[PDB]
Amino acid sequence: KTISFNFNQFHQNEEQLKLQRDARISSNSVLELTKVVNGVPTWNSTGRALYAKPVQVWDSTTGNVASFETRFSFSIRQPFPRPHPADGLVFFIAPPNTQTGEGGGYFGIYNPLSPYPFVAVEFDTFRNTWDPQIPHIGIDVNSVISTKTVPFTLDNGGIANVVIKYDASTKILHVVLVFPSLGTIYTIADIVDLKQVLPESVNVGFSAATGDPSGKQRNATETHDILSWSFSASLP
Amino acid sequence: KTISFNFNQFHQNEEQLKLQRDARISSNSVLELTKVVNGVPTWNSTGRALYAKPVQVWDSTTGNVASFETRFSFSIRQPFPRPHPADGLVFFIAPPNTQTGEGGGYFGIYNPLSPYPFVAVEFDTFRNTWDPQIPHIGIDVNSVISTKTVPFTLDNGGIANVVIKYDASTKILHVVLVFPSLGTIYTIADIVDLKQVLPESVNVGFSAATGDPSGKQRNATETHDILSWSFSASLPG
Ligand SMILES: *[C@@H]1O[C@H](CO)[C@@H](O[C@@H]2O[C@H](CO)[C@@H](O)[C@H](O)[C@H]2NC(C)=O)[C@H](O[C@@H]2O[C@@H](C)[C@@H](O)[C@@H](O)[C@@H]2O)[C@H]1NC(C)=O
Ligand SMILES: *[C@@H]1O[C@H](CO)[C@@H](O[C@@H]2O[C@H](CO)[C@@H](O)[C@H](O)[C@H]2NC(C)=O)[C@H](O[C@@H]2O[C@@H](C)[C@@H](O)[C@@H](O)[C@@H]2O)[C@H]1NC(C)=O
Ligand SMILES: *[C@@H]1O[C@H](CO)[C@@H](O[C@@H]2O[C@H](CO)[C@@H](O)[C@H](O)[C@H]2NC(C)=O)[C@H](O[C@@H]2O[C@@H](C)[C@@H](O)[C@@H](O)[C@@H]2O)[C@H]1NC(C)=O
Ligand SMILES: *[C@@H]1O[C@H](CO)[C@@H](O[C@@H]2O[C@H](CO)[C@@H](O)[C@H](O)[C@H]2NC(C)=O)[C@H](O[C@@H]2O[C@@H](C)[C@@H](O)[C@@H](O)[C@@H]2O)[C@H]1NC(C)=O
Ligand SMILES: CC(=O)N[C@H]1[C@@H](O[C@@H]2[C@@H](O)[C@@H](O)O[C@H](CO)[C@@H]2O)O[C@H](CO)[C@H](O)[C@@H]1O
Ligand SMILES: CC(=O)N[C@H]1[C@@H](O[C@@H]2[C@@H](O)[C@@H](O)O[C@H](CO)[C@@H]2O)O[C@H](CO)[C@H](O)[C@@H]1O
Ligand SMILES: [Ca+2]
Ligand SMILES: [Ca+2]
Ligand SMILES: [Mn+2]
Ligand SMILES: [Mn+2]
């Protein structure tokens, strides 16, 4: 069984996407996860975008787990350097029919009141108490306290290409981050047993958030745009 | 106990490098692993380049294994599309004081007569009986029959950036291949227990080869140039 989709760009009312909270598609075809008014990103924003159809990551009958590969391009523009941009964006896999969780450093995927399991790859731009220096790429399993982390230098407003690959036979999740304009390459990998943390059917998508009001800083913001996205999964 | 070296270019007769067989450094500073005469790559060629000093990847006293990262840029130019360029190049780790092995699809690292252990990342351009479609990246452990493989499309004569990383805590060896002119990205990873296959001290370097005479095709060739190379390893204790 193989499932795959490709998005060279994004259109309004796209039927294959499920937009939640502040997420929306601009007229020039970009998926803006967090609020941007008149070219200016705002604080207190959270938004998600899920693929409309659930994907089967493993089968309880055969015990087999799926392998998958997803590539996407994003752009983070940080117009206000002081005091600190926030919060970042993530690619995540979660049970279907979930709802946006808490914003801020929780990226909109974690809900303390009723936590659901999830695997996520974060591009964290704000250093919370539980964080190492930012920006960093992090692999999260059921929590935003990354199992593995790697730092990177953001190309402010530039385009970033990401490749996430998961091999079921080795349980290796490897992610590659490239900034073509700068020619920089960052890589991180870890062992994650999907079958052990997630249910057979899941949703895949993105989530992001800007500074939470509790921080009392309106400058704690930045854009979180997704320019393209392709996904592929194979369940033998 | 970190160790690291960086070559942003290659000088004529590098005191830090050991060149074997056909490997040589051109006047414009590139490390040519296989023979090129008058701008034309030839067949029947094999060459290696090792860092002159051995590196310790693990310590029997503490049992600790080293983590490392290496980056390099290479370029493979294929002048003759038909009937099939050959053979490819590899980055390898082997016991010190070894000798060039068999050429052809063995890249110069495998010696059937007297095999020595090795871990290598290959960029294979010729499809041997044991190979999947080419070109492909492959992870080799003690043999050229890759444990893992992934295909890629070569940027003929272009520059390629490679990042190889090994994390001792997870035993994950991940390699990334990027062709900046094309913007293409390829990735592959696998679990490899260095401590279990290699000795405490090893050599790190490159090896490559062009078509073997047995193939009876002088067109089975291509260049195998290394443009730059940096290495870094951390052995806690
Ligand atoms: C952060 O954004 C939230 C919505 O994205 C704001 O809450 C919502 O505000 C709407 C307009 O005031 C209101 O109709 C909704 O009921 C409310 N949602 C709920 C129930 O929480 C949130 O704060 C609100 O709006 C500001 C302008 C003040 O009026 C507050 O008293 C509201 O709770 C925004 N945070 C802030 C303080 O900007
Ligand atoms: C939030 O972002 C604002 C826009 O960058 C900051 O103001 C800008 O500060 C610059 C020097 O840091 C100054 O050259 C710009 O003119 C100014 N832009 C405008 C029109 O606000 C702002 O910094 C604070 O406010 C400015 C006006 C100065 O008083 C600074 O000393 C203040 O820090 C940022 N606010 C915070 C809390 O950093
Ligand atoms: C080995 O590579 C050579 C260079 O690409 C091939 O010759 C070239 O073949 C072209 C058509 O394939 C032809 O337009 C070119 O004029 C010619 N170039 C030269 C320098 O000869 C060669 O192809 C074969 O051998 C040559 C001598 C011709 O007889 C071709 O028709 C043959 O296909 C390549 N060898 C093989 C066996 O493919
Ligand atoms: C393939 O490359 C080999 C070098 O690694 C050639 O080996 C030959 O080794 C001889 C022993 O020291 C040396 O004198 C020769 O110069 C050298 N090749 C030549 C002619 O330059 C090999 O050459 C073939 O095999 C040798 C043993 C002789 O019989 C030569 O006449 C043959 O050409 C190269 N083979 C081919 C197909 O070119
Ligand atoms: C958990 C969370 O959403 N944190 C966000 C918040 O960080 C805290 C802030 O709430 C308050 O407690 O002060 C501390 C520093 O003493 C932190 O800023 O706000 C920032 C933006 O200002 C960001 O959104 C965090 O993710
Ligand atoms: C093992 C080896 O080095 N093989 C090289 C050889 O490939 C084979 C050749 O052995 C013979 O059997 O013919 C077949 C095709 O029917 C292959 O060519 O030669 C090629 C060069 O053409 C290459 O160097 C192989 O790696
Ligand atoms: Ca954070
Ligand atoms: Ca081969
Ligand atoms: Mn984080
Ligand atoms: Mn191969």
Image: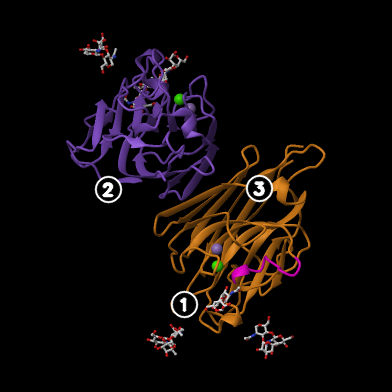
Chain colours: A purple, B orange
The location of residue A216, given as percent across then percent down, is: 37, 14
Q: What subunit carries mark 3? A: B
Upstream in the sequence, badge 1 or badge 3?
1
Residue receiving disc 2? A8
Residue A67 located within the stretch drawn in magenta? no
Nearer-the-camera pick, B119 or A41: B119
Secondary structure beneath label 1: loop
Mark 2 surroundings within 10 Å by alpha-carbon count, few (fewer than 14), some (14 through 19), many (20 or more): few
Q: How far apart are marks 1 and 3 (CA)?
A: 34 Å
Is A11 situated left or right of A147 in this image?
left
B151 vs B22: above or below: above
Q: How far apart are marks 2 and 3 (CA)?
A: 38 Å
Residue receiving disc 3? B232
Q: Mark 3 is on which residue type?
A: Ser
Q: Distance between the residues labelled 1 and 2?
A: 34 Å
Main SS of the magenta part reads loop
The location of residue B223, given as percent across then percent down, is: 54, 72
The location of residue B24, given as percent across then percent down, is: 65, 72
Kindly report which numbered mark, 1 or 3, lies closer to the viewer in this rendering: 1
Please tell me which residue is depicted at 46% across the width and 77% down the height of the picture.
B79
Q: Give the range drawn in magenta.
A: B105-114
Callouts 1 and 2 on one subunit? no
